[PDB]
Image (tube, rainbow, N blue to C red; front, top):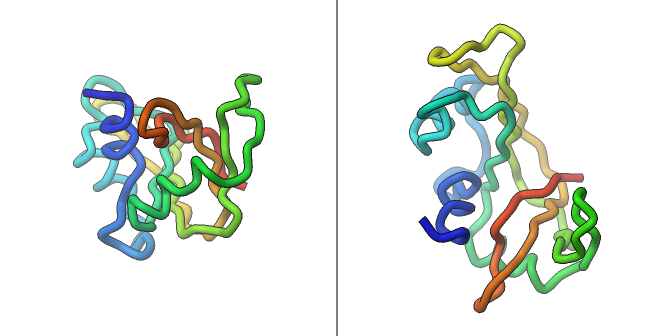
Length: 123
């Protein structure tokens, strides 16, 4: 999987405008194969077109949590869903708490074309 394709599979959900119900995370973490060998503890889904998320790589340049400087903050807020494993969750029965919000996103970009390859944070 290329780095760009793995970001789309783990974080893009342009088919919905927002998380619907409290089971959204349990369903999406499973269908995007993030519960496959372990339960990915934290993951964010972005409800905007791929083009709008790719445009973030040309917006506000900021440092990544790791100190690298190829991170970019979106100028506007975007609809996002934060999925966090519950203290109860245990592989293979992964359980997640769903939180829907509109926030700025921060992504790490790379390559040519320069597109998102990691989701750093939401603010």
